[PDB]
Length: 155
Image (spheres, rainbow, N blue to C red):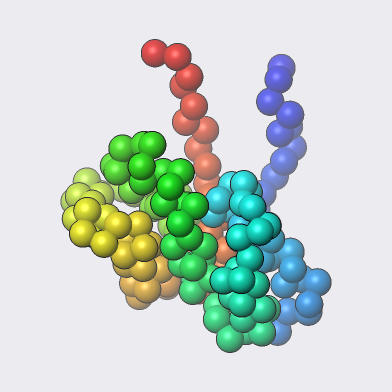
C-alpha cells in the first residue's frame, strides 16, 4: 500500500546533552525545527534563529528554551492560531511540547485561558517553564512527537 514509512522507527530522541560534539549538535538543532514546525521554515528567517542556534550549540540555552523560541516564532502563530480554531492550535501546542498531546479536560480549558490571554507565546512558555513538564520530557530532549495519525480527510 501507499504510505512509504514502512520501517521508519523513531525511538531516536534528539537530546542536547551538555557534552555533545559539534556535528551531533547540528543534528539535534535541525531535528528541533523538524519536530516543532514539521520542517517548513524559510532560511531567510535567520538572525533570531542564528543567535539561538549558536547559543544551544554553545550550551548557553537548553532545548527547553530553544523549543520555546521556535514555538514563539510569528510563523508558528500565523499557520495555526489564525486558519484553525484555537482549541485545535492548543491541542497542537500540547502535542508538540509534551510530545504526545493533552489528557485532562480541565488542563485543556486551563491553558485555553492562557492562549486566550497571551496567545501561543504565553501558552508554550507555560508548557516548557513548568517544573512538571521540564521533569517529564526533560530540558535536554527535543519534543519528539508520538504522532498518532489523525487525518480522516473527507466528512
